[PDB]
Image (cartoon, rainbow over all chains, first blue to last red; front, side):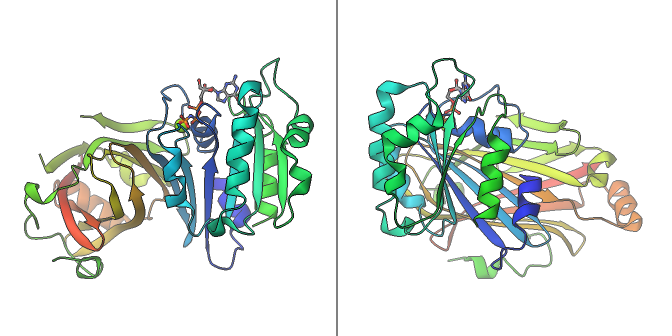
Length: 175
Length: 161
Ligand SMILES: Nc1nc2c(ncn2[C@@H]2O[C@H](COP(=O)(O)OP(=O)(O)NP(=O)(O)O)[C@@H](O)[C@H]2O)c(=O)[nH]1
Ligand SMILES: [Mg+2]
């Protein structure tokens, strides 16, 4: 997050708000703690939000992780305002939930408060052997039909860190 | 009807608590506080748990450069609109650090965390030894607002011996 801040520091408003969404169990909080260089061992399901507010030289990087459980999801809308980047996380090995996650992503990309917001899709848990590759997830979700914004899909493992920096590098280039 | 405006220019610690416990109608509850050095990764302090805290810290805290400060809080049955936190640290009429964070909506019966990751202000040797020599004269106010109205006020003093 520290170096990410420095990679975004040229942003004219001097603040960047990143929203982390995705189904419960996708790996959102793990990703957040990975980015924050924090121990990822005490993680439980998020019944609310987790925020990292990174502030240096009057620049402000706020990353919001909202819980993904079905009972928390209806509140996602309460956190859309002033979002600069959406990061949408998917468990690449949970195929039974591919349709559920496509549905949620579809809704997000129709939301008035998220219009034109760049979206990074993290195809997470690539360390798992049964994980679908990013290209396959992209095909399944019809990411090529996205008209109204820049987007990227990135293979990653929030657990190991692999692919995470490549995703965040795209984010930094597209703020 | 105390508001953010009343608090943002203060040059010293409040004289006394600014509200009663009963004014916390949303049952907001701070259950954990953690301080870590972002450089070495070391957790310098964590507490896992009534509106006053006395912190027993060391001089090493004052020589840090990159700090992560986490709060963890629960919310009761009622949804909270426009939750805002303002925290201010002082030593003897000087403002050391200020944090103003607009949480916005808080989900009913939620458990939430916020970590402020920041550049520790480079305090002069004069100031550092002065605060080391005078324990508990470094103090903080934590103000919590719901829709611009103060609903909770916590206080702390600090020792760096
Ligand atoms: N194998 C593997 N497991 C991962 C990876 N990322 C997260 N996990 C695991 O997936 C489970 C859920 O992770 P978590 O970060 O809590 O997901 P979440 O999206 O925050 N869930 P919620 O929205 O309910 O808080 C945890 O057991 C976590 O260790 C990954 O990249 N690889
Ligand atoms: Mg979580």
